[PDB]
Amino acid sequence: AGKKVLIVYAHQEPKSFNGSLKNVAVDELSRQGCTVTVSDLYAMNFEPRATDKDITGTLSNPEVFNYGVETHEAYKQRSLASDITDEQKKVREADLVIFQFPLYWFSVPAILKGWMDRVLCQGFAFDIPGFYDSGLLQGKLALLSVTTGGTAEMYTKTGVNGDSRYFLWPLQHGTLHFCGFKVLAPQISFAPEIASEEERKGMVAAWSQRLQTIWKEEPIPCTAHWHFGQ
Amino acid sequence: AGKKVLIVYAHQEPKSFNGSLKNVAVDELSRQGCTVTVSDLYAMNFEPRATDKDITGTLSNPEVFNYGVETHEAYKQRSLASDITDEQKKVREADLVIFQFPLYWFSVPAILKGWMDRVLCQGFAFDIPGFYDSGLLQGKLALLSVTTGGTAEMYTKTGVNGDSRYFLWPLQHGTLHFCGFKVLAPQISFAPEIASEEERKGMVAAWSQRLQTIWKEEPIPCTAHWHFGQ
Ligand SMILES: Cc1cc2nc3c(=O)[nH]c(=O)nc-3n(C[C@H](O)[C@H](O)[C@H](O)COP(=O)(O)OP(=O)(O)OC[C@H]3O[C@@H](n4cnc5c(N)ncnc54)[C@H](O)[C@@H]3O)c2cc1C
Ligand SMILES: Cc1cc2nc3c(=O)[nH]c(=O)nc-3n(C[C@H](O)[C@H](O)[C@H](O)COP(=O)(O)OP(=O)(O)OC[C@H]3O[C@@H](n4cnc5c(N)ncnc54)[C@H](O)[C@@H]3O)c2cc1C
Ligand SMILES: Cc1cc(=O)n(C)c2c3c(ccc12)OCO3
Ligand SMILES: Cc1cc(=O)n(C)c2c3c(ccc12)OCO3
Ligand SMILES: [Zn+2]
Ligand SMILES: [Zn+2]
Image (cartoon, rainbow over the protein chains, first blue to last red):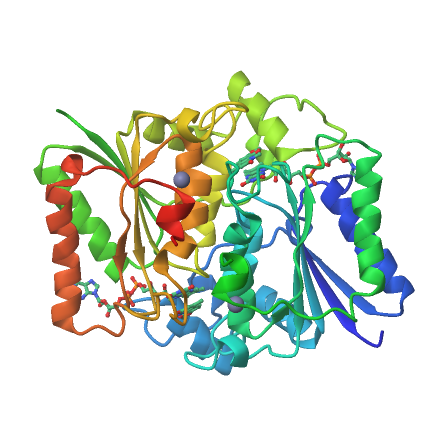
């Protein structure tokens, strides 16, 4: 309040722990007066593939299809497919984008990778060049809220998975920061599946709690040294 | 010896630089007398979404759908969807898997991320426990062949985009090594669209030339140190 929040949510099951974290993010920010929108990608059957159907009407060059060039020209000429233009308007208006997802292979599920390949297009997200700290979406906050199968200890620098910031890098720096976002600190709920149940309700409530002061937070100093450095 | 290769390929335009790197891989390994298979994900309209459509049997927990639990059970039961089992059969038989793709947001295009999410399921590619050096696909080689928009210097330490290896981590270590593969050194073909004809032509021949000696190669030490250093 008086802010707009988009939650991009990527889980198949409403009773999941991811559902719960999305449902408290809605409740708590609703409570505070914020304007809230949720893109439930599985329930929308969101199309993850970057293809020629993403451009309506006719293309610059049907001899050799280049996806980046074509989507860029289609953004400028307002001829993107409507699923994409709908998401862009939500992002455009949002002051905070929250991504709520289970970690798949040290990254986002494919349905959410496709939202990012398709919606964050050239002309809207960034414009080769006019990027990083000057990316087209500067002023907006972005926040990853990730659940993991693996425990907190596995995600340290000398444990099996290496350090959490290592996988964060393509998402946080290569995507969010590249587009102009200022990135709040990931929220990582480590290993909900191996409960309890008690410790679940508490991970959830720390999420609720943190969202009480979300607007006070400072953005991470988005650098190579934050993700890897000493 | 006789060898089987799978090329998992993710570009939309047969005439692209990616198309050409894939075709010369086919020509060169074909010429050596290797068995070669290409999964052309876009021409297959490959399904990247991990949904409950991926299980044809009675669900293990039909009240609360968890994708990892259900695909693991579906795999032991032989109740996965046929597109997934067709890919697993190609991977199972392959001695080498080459991924051929344009970098999208510091990672794979979503259609390829969906191949990772849905094909590399628990019970086939890995087990809890039975991961990293004990992953189920032990024995097999894997190689990333990645094209970029950025140079060829932007991809160093400082370094607009940071070191190239930073973004390889989730793919190489978190996915491939985790499934037991030994990973060979990425083929990164920087900035083809900027590049002039002599540089394109020669990037294409440098790949051809490298494949001549591919079974002579040793895998990378797939570590935090290789990826990040210092
Ligand atoms: C393809 C694939 C790739 C993967 N790659 C990785 C990886 O790279 N790294 C990694 O660490 N893990 C990985 N995983 C594992 C995955 O990240 C975890 O399975 C997932 O994050 C668990 O979250 P969930 O929301 O789906 O759990 P859920 O099982 O849906 O939730 C956990 C439990 O909490 C319960 N619950 C729901 N809401 C509440 C609430 N309100 N209060 C109390 N309890 C509640 C649920 O009913 C359930 O019992 C991968 C999994 C898959 C399927
Ligand atoms: C959603 C999205 C996200 C992206 N994210 C990133 C990112 O994170 N980092 C980054 O660096 N880049 C990124 N890019 C840029 C992208 O990776 C490049 O556009 C891509 O790697 C170029 O490969 P291509 O095959 O499409 O090149 P093409 O445009 O197809 O190749 C350029 C030229 O090569 C020619 N060619 C093909 N074969 C040959 C041949 N054998 N001999 C001579 N010429 C040939 C073609 O005719 C063409 O004219 C992103 C792009 C998109 C669309
Ligand atoms: C890469 C990875 C690391 C990890 O710590 N865990 C628990 C994983 C997992 C998967 C797939 C990948 C991983 O499915 C269920 O649990
Ligand atoms: C993250 C990134 C780094 C980069 O160096 N380049 C060229 C990019 C690009 C994209 C999207 C992201 C990137 O579309 C066209 O070129
Ligand atoms: Zn950054
Ligand atoms: Zn590794």
